[PDB]
Amino acid sequence: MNAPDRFELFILPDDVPKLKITPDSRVPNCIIIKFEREDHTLANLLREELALYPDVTFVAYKVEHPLFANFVMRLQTEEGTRPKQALERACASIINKLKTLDHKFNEEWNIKN
Amino acid sequence: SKEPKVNIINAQDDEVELMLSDVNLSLANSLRRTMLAEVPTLAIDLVEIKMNTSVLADEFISHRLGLIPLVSEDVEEMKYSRDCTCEDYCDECSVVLELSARHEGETTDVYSSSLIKVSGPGNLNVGEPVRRDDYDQGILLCKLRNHQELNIRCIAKKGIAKEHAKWSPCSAIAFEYDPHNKLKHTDFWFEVDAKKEWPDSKYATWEEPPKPGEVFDYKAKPNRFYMTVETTGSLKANQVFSRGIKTLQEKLANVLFELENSRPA
Amino acid sequence: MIIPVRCFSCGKVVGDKWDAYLRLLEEGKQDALDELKLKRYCCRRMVLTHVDLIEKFLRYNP
Amino acid sequence: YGVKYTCGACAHNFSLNKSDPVRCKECGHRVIYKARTKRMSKFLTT
Ligand SMILES: [Zn+2]
Ligand SMILES: [Zn+2]
Ligand SMILES: [Zn+2]
């Protein structure tokens, strides 16, 4: 009756970017990234790998409200180092970790009877 | 070989126990849910009933078939009806099925085995009534009496567990870590003795016991996770792990891709 | 009212398992669930609680 | 090809119109259902 169409939990709707990045005025060298059609599955994973770049001064994320599949990610880094980059890096470190995983799980498997 | 590492334990066709070490829980969990919800599959989605004298109603059966597990091997070389340039559907993005059931044998049953595959499979593993039943007719759709008929026509499509549960190929997944509460990520309830009143897990044997004389370790983090990946069919227990590991990756990709599309301007 | 394909709770299929069960009773006189491969109670309760009405419905004429 | 009304018991395709009585080709039992449609009905699998 009033509930959305299921496919609104992953498909971007009419003109909408996965990412929208906004500068934060509250404190220097900080940003808030709006991720559209996403959740903890991906949020918390990005949040995590950032407290890994000891070059990142801050990193938390949140789901405004459960009805809407979106989420905000706030990042702040050291001097003259752009967080967006740290987002790239910490994001890449993620794929590799998984790239390795995929592989280590395949050779491993074959050795089964 | 490199970063995180696996160490499979007893594994079969409908399960895959294994230990995942050298990874942040955060990341284990992420993969956890990804299997549970976002791996492309193939389920019946549209049902065009023609005749039906069964005691079950139209949409009741319709539901049923939505759940019947279909093949989803080369599910990846098919397209989402939403992206296919064909008005409605076609061989390039769907699998059509037939079902005819006339009551002749004066209780006749309708098993998922009774499904035809009227459209062109284009020579790719997909659209098959996954049967694991001992006899050879897995999933009793429904029963019917004397002269009750029933003619359908199903159309299957890609989709995922987000869109609907009728998709996710996961179906239950075990997850545990640090069986001996060393990290103290829990405060055991108890009347007198926590340890005696709280069942010890079968997982406590691949990690060393506590050892009293030691003070509380703090700098230690959640490393190593004992899991188990059950499958319902559609995709091989192994893949339901691989593909998972990969889709999560594809997503992490666009987050980096979408990124790039925003630097030029 | 027929058997429920796949368990609500976890998801594991369970449509086929009906006849196997209702059989391991009548004859083998038996636990049944356990061998049918129905481990954790979520799916367990699924089978062990189904009351197959369809049978009685089927007893009706046209 | 073609069917109009059916009987509550002896499900035998009938067919009528005004004043032609409201019974059946035998059984007096004056019930009768109005058999399914020709235009197929389309369903969703959720
Ligand atoms: Zn198409
Ligand atoms: Zn279950
Ligand atoms: Zn009559």
Image (cartoon, rainbow, N blue to C red):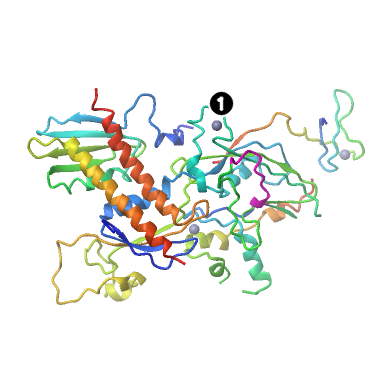
Confirm if mark 1 falls within 8 A of ligand 1: no
**Residue B65 in picture, x, y percent from top left:** 60, 45
Q: x and y percent of residue C38 in the render?
A: 52, 64
- Quadrant including the N terminus of chain B: bottom left
Q: Tell me if residue B113 is in the magenta stretch.
A: yes
Q: Measured from the top left, where is residue A32 in percent x and y?
A: 20, 34
Picture quadrant where residue B253 is located: top left
Q: Which residue is mark 1?
A: B87
Around disc 1, counting alpha carbons within 10 Å, would you say few (fewer than 14), some (14 to 19), or many (20 or more)? few
Residue B146 located left or right of residue B15:
right
Taking the spot 26% from the left edge, 32% from the top edge, the residue there is B259
Pick the front one: B230 or B107: B230
In the depicted structure, whether residue B18 falls above or below residue B24: below
Q: Amino acid at mark 1?
A: Glu
Name the chain under label 1. Answer: B
Q: Which residues are magenta?
A: B111-122
Whether B10 is among the magenta residues is: no
Q: Quadrant of the C terminus of chain B?
A: top left
Q: Quadrant location of ligand 3? A: top right
Whether residue B186 appears in this view of the structure is yes
Please state the horizontal and vertical placement of residue D34, each as a whole percent of the image: 77, 32
